[PDB]
Amino acid sequence: GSMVKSGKARAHTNIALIKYWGKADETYIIPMNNSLSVTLDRFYTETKVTFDPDFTEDCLILNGNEVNAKEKEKIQNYMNIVRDLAGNRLHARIESENYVPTAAGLASSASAYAALAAACNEALSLNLSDTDLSRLARRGSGSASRSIFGGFAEWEKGHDDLTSYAHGINSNGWEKDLSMIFVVINNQSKKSRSGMSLTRDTSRFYQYWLDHVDEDLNEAKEAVKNQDFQRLGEVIEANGLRMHATNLGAQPPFTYLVQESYDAMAIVEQCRKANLPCYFTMDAGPNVKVLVEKKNKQAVMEQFLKVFDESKIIASDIISSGVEIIK
Amino acid sequence: VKSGKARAHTNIALIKYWGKADETYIIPMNNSLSVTLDRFYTETKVTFDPDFTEDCLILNGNEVNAKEKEKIQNYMNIVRDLAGNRLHARIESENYVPTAAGLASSASAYAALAAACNEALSLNLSDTDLSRLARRGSGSASRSIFGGFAEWEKGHDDLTSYAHGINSNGWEKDLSMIFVVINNQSKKVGMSLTRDTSRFYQYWLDHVDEDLNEAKEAVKNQDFQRLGEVIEANGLRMHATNLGAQPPFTYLVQESYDAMAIVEQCRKANLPCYFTMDAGPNVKVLVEKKNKQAVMEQFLKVFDESKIIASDIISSGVEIIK
């Protein structure tokens, strides 16, 4: 229509190699430390927003379905940020499709909020910089800040809303040579922000995390500058494990990992011993993610396919480009 | 024929033994602190007969696995060497523990065997040397020579590595331990792997001496909360080391964490108690006698009666039978 402003964006999920875990500020989503991720080619969210003066409230339709009273409230609060930023009072119909294996445990929050932020920027012609786009995404989900970018990306922690945001890291095309295999681990179906908060606030091992994160980050970044896969893998695997260690120290303790997760880790180590370099990481759940060079992707997958169902071994390459405006 | 019989009780480490400096003589990377338990024990009769060609172990009325025989035969060589004879022995041990519940018996088994041999061969070993003898079979056995609180001093060789009993002016008579029996998901079955390969092991080493000092200070002052907090943190740091092993592993399962959550709730409800876990998923809850029944009731809301088993802390140490 004449008075109608719409925009549509595709943004890809990302997986943190140096973990985001713990917030300095719950309201504005400011983290305790910097994080480093890779953006996945295979998994993404497409989101259209349509702002119409006649709309009375924001509507969200997800994968063709209404969301419910609760998720509807969360989205309306986020859109208030957008309206304020834009200096208007328009409401939007949001139609989003996740092309992310969510039932298999993969998170869609990073792609979702990045897609939405970009979609709004397009619909309203805000001409936001990548930095400001990153800051807007961050308000929805911290990891979404990084999904504005392709390849390697880093979320700079900052100290406030203006200074906390992400940027893309140029790696001389190295991202084109890397892959990530997702091992879908059998998990309970019972109902990440709550856990992170409990650990950050109460964990007896949280200081240990803080004492090593910057060192890990620098080492990781040095490894990327050298395209040194083993140096990257060793530090990110250790960093990932330290993050899980912090949960063990929470009051009371908890874990995201199950025995099956440890089985998958054992297979990665076996691959390293059989001259197939690869390294694992885990987030707020038992799924195991395996960083591997693209040339070795298939051979590592086959080692997994000996133990696990074919449907549970899902690989993705790493995409070079960032968030995109689509039809 | 020469024979003797002895009873030794299990002990639970509050400051963990985790990692060896020397595998051959079982010298640890750090000191450990434990409490000895009233309810769980091993009784062992040993009989040295010149007739016997090889050492025989019969446990709970049944022969032991091939691997255990080899262990016993090696351990018995140490005894023969210390005694200065060439006698083989039939060993008849009985473990008094809940069946198939995952409770360890190596500490009580070897402490009972060492004392049984001490008696049979009339060595009149001092407590120190009896503890030394027990250590060669199993590190924790060094501590079961004693009751109440006991500390294993790591030393630096065979002569200097041993345990002693800690006098807490009877404080142990005021304390108890509730076991929460939990099982894993494996139909069929770490310290070395973790000591040798864990990326977080230095973290353990950096804090253990401090924990130990804080723990010993608490005992001296009979300060339950202070003891509890440091031992709980220490036990968790031990399990953290396993997460950094190459490749990582865990002794814990979700039900273990379920039990830990109950302890924390008890603390919030004016029922001070603290947990620790060893090389398995069972959760052990230290609690003062006055609060044992109340804390048990809280567990009974979630866990089955058959899976909650309490023990007092015994004051006396290893003991000759007859």
Image: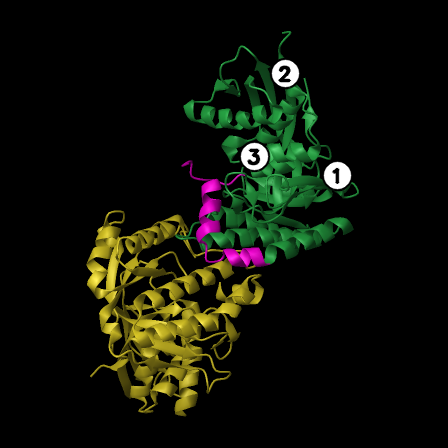
Chain colours: A green, B yellow
Residue furthest to the top in view is: A2
Q: Which residue is mark 2?
A: A6
What's the distance in space between the residues labelled 1 and 3, CA to CA?
30 Å
Secondary structure at badge 2 equals strand
- In primary-sequence order, the first of circles 2 and 1 is 2
Q: Which residues are magenta?
A: A184-211
Q: Which of the 4 image quarters holds residue A86? A: top right
Q: Which residue is mark 1?
A: A176
- Is residue B31 something that shows in the picture? yes
Crowding at mark 2 (Cα within 10 Å: few <14, some 14-19, many 20+): many
At 47% from the left and 46% from the top, the residue drawn is A197
Q: Chain of mark 2?
A: A
Q: Chain of mark 1?
A: A
What's the distance in space between the residues labelled 2 and 1, CA to CA?
33 Å
Q: Which of the 4 image quarters holds residue A142? A: top right
A70 and A121: which is toward the camera: A121
Residue type marked 3: Arg
Question: Would you place residue B138 above or below residue B240 in this image?
Answer: below
Q: Position of residue B9 (x, y in %)?
A: 29, 73
- In primary-sequence order, the first of circles 3 and 2 is 2
Secondary structure at badge 1 equals helix
At 41% from the left and 77% from the top, the residue drawn is B137
Q: Is residue A79 magenta?
A: no
Q: Which residue is mark 3?
A: A139
Q: Is residue B54 left or right of residue B223?
A: right
